[PDB]
Image (cartoon, coloured by chain):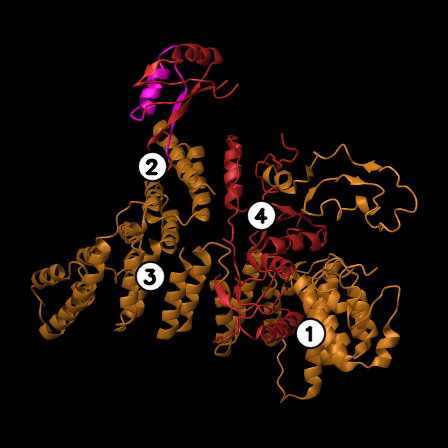
Amino acid sequence: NNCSIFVGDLAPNVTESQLFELFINRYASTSHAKIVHDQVTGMSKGYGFVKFTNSDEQQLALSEMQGVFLNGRAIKVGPTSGMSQFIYPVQQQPSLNHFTDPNNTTVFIGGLSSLVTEDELRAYFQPFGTIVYVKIPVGKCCGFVQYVDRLSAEAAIAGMQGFPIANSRVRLSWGRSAKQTALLQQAMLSNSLQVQQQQPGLQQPNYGYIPSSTCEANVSSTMLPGCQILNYSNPQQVIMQGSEAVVNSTNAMLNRLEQGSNGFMFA
Amino acid sequence: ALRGLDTQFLQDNTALVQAYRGLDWSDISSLTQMVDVIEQTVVKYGNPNDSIKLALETILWQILRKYPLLFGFWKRFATIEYQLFGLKKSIAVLATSVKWFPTSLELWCDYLNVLCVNNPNETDFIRNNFEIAKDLIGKQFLSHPFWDKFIEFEVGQKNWHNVQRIYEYIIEVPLHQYARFFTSYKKFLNEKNLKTTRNIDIVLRKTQTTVNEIWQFESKIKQPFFNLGQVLNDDLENWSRYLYHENTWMMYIKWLTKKNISDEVVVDIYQKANTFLPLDFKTLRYDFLRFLKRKYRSNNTLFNNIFNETVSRYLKIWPNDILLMTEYLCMLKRHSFKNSLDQSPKEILEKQTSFTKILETSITNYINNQIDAKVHLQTLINDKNLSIVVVELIKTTWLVLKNNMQTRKYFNLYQKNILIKNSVPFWLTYYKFEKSNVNFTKLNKFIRELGVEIYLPTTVMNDILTDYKTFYLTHSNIVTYESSIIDSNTFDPILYPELKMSNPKYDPVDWHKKTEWKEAGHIGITTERPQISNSIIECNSGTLIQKPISLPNFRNLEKINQVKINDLYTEEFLKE
């Protein structure tokens, strides 16, 4: 029941050890003893709580220690325990799988043709946002794409849901990494716990980055708000955003059109 | 895959023949079959490989015992242990003996004699030579072993100066200057070898591999390249590779290309790196293809056949890859149908029409599922790689023979096939064709269809919409644009590419039960949320006072706690 008695008017040279000694091993074996000391001064405030397991043990302690001389005083052992309209809410926690993790930014692309490569799968999912990795298993007919942003991954699940990649309607949803999948597979063949770990945060406030933004390749930028200052490099490292993003982008897409028409990239 | 279980099975099957004490022709052939299945699966390191050669030699199968030795030489370059055994055997042989015994000896001498631990190999050949009475032949091996930086070089020098009582110093000056120059190099090489001899220790670590010192040893034998180098860096690569690492192969090939030996040596090294290296590396392989294209200009006929067998072997293992098919087809158009400008034009045009004829009969043959293995292109077509053959046929029919009617007939036929309706170079060639003719009707009908019924990768759809907007703005006037606007699709070629860019599934033109409502704040997690049926929050309070407000009707009050998830991940991939 964790029955608590509130001893008070204690002497200054009486310890929590002595308060345990006068509470535990007489009439009970009390679960805890805690004198309130001063939070910066250390000198005991003269009152402290003790926590007995059983309520009969505490009341037996209460009737017998009332007035009992402890290190020079009578230690006043009254029981500690046993209408606003508005209170703040309180809620449970959804136990952190891959769906209920608010930082999970890796899409599970399922139902692939198995005739689709990794570069051809990078070509679909790239303009939604910058992309850390696109590895796919050998013949499980399903892939894995991971973005830097949660916003870009949500845009990819919205925009590319049910789109056919090489004539098979694709199945997009959430799903963990390769390390976490190996961990869950071995701890599911041992079926012990299969608990997951939260994906790492960006340690915000972060000021340079405007999420869901791509730049493909000397900088004196005026660092003003409307522009973009920092960015993630495409695979990986962080680049200061140059002035000439559109020239490099448009020039690379004219390159991509003229080389893809003749056959040097199927992506 | 289980090389340990493949090691364990041969260790178990051999222990079944050995402990049942019989010849055991089942288990003898099973241990041989387990040896063949392993050696095809694994490179078979020489220490493990020797037991297989020892058991077959114990089973007295002389012709087969020679053949497994050749495989061992390919598997391990530093296999002096297999080299000496193959030299120790085949001396107990038939009439071809005297020629074969030196042939294996000299082949090892071009394989292993530049190693620091090669002192046993020359001595064994010397032992073979001293058993003969060709003291001239013994003398020739003595001078060659003197000139190479070997372990017991001083031990070899003094020994050869006492056994050769008849002809010791016929040329004193020549022998000792070659010996001391060998000692200058071996003193130099002693720095790297002792730095290697003090790191190699099997503790399952980087020191057992000695990769830092092996990269140190290979580097310092690269720069001071006194022409033993190409044999030495081969010997340096051989001890360093044996300790799969493709970057070491690339550095050895880069050095040997810079050293400019004849190219067939490089082709041998390239074939070996093709053979023993694991699949999916995909970087030395395309290097080999572009080396075969570059060196094609020097010698014509054999490089076409090396190229052809290479591209066939690489569509064995990467069938989903498409750059090989167009690369094969570029080489076929260059080599088999070649015709310069200086030739009379009817010859030129007939070679173009022959190429169109073979290419069209190839794709028409493969669609109707009849194959013709005499023509190599028929074998090479894969359904991932069919589209690039159709593209080559289109681009050759339209740009070379120059008839637009036949070209439009091929487009209108092949865009209905299953294999190539979703292919990128077919449709992007179609875009360049209907851009060449400047008509906009087919282009507007194409990009109006680009998300719904012609499925392309989003990077290609973005490129097509951007370039078509840039093209339309500069090649079309308002009188064409305002007559191009039709209202049932709300299509307008100025603004519709600007809206259709990142979302492919874009339709241009009971809400509470759609799958955009139900998972509104949180994607993927679907919850039917409670709501009031007749809410008044759109109604102003200036109009609520006119008549009294009804009670609220509710919907979905049972489901404030129910939240449900379609977990594709666990079902289709964790639990298969």
**Chain B drawn colour:** orange
Q: Residues within 10 Å of mark 3 (few under 14, many from 20)?
A: many
Residue A29 lies within the magenta run: yes
Query: Does residue B64 lie above or below B27 as drawn?
Result: below
Report the front residue among B213 and B512.
Answer: B512
Instruction: Kindly identify which numbered label has been placed on residue A41.
Output: 2
Element type where label 1 sits in the image: helix
In front of the other: label 3 or label 4? 4
Q: Earlier in the sequence, mark 1 or mark 3?
A: 3
Tell me the CA gap for discs 3 and 2. 73 Å
In front of the other: label 1 or label 2? 2
- The lab-note entry on whether marks 3 and 4 share a chain reads no
Instruction: Kindly identify which numbered label has been placed on residue B237.
Output: 3
The chain to which mark 2 is attached is: A
Amino acid found under the numbered disc labelled 1 = Phe
Q: Residue at x 87, y 51 (%)?
A: B542
